[PDB]
Length: 236
Length: 10
Ligand SMILES: CC1(C)CCC(C)(C)c2cc(C(=O)Nc3ccc(C(=O)O)cc3)ccc21
Image (cartoon, rainbow over all chains, first blue to last red; front, side, top):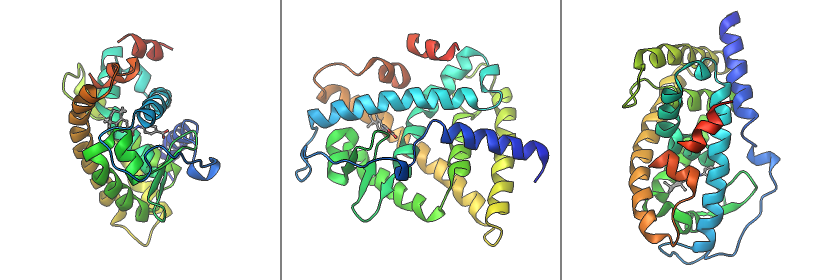
């Protein structure tokens, strides 16, 4: 309702919407690659999943550049923030396209993989935690504004190690947390417990992405060639 | 950091 808050919300909702196609807009398609048998790693699934992740990293960087004040931080701190939040944002995005009935997740080109295929594509031991998080996310009934704000709050975090200006990042995050709080109450006034519940997802996300950093390690051993360039930059 | 940068630098 405040003029400054409304503009911040509009900017972040627009940033998310313009870098994230919704499940409803996409034409779902399946693949037969080890859809029924669990394996350590399906090579054809890995190549598709690694390429889709590369494209999604590019979109996350485009999203970050549209968040107010992000491009005003040092290049060193933008890089530190993007690398620290990389897996958190990709995981929140893949989990936003969850279909409970078929237990599938849909990627940005429409590729829809079941629990077994997500496991075989490279998730492995991460799979049940990612799918549990998707199920916890679903009842929250979040819209573009809230998903976008959750992504911006996860990226713009002062607690990341090796930040040249952590207090500057802390200051930049505060207007986003305030904007999320008022928007959640304005959109859903009957349930005032939703705001700290949404923030709990960020803690779960950090926990899943900490395990995810260990999965990058075990995957580098299993995959034939080296990791794609951009993925190596973000996670190594 | 390459990529990144690129990216960035914008
Ligand atoms: C840690 C692990 C297993 C290995 C390293 C990579 C491959 C970087 C990775 C990537 C994701 C991921 O979520 N990628 C996404 C790809 C595309 C979309 C989209 O199109 O919306 C969203 C997410 C998850 C885990 C991992």
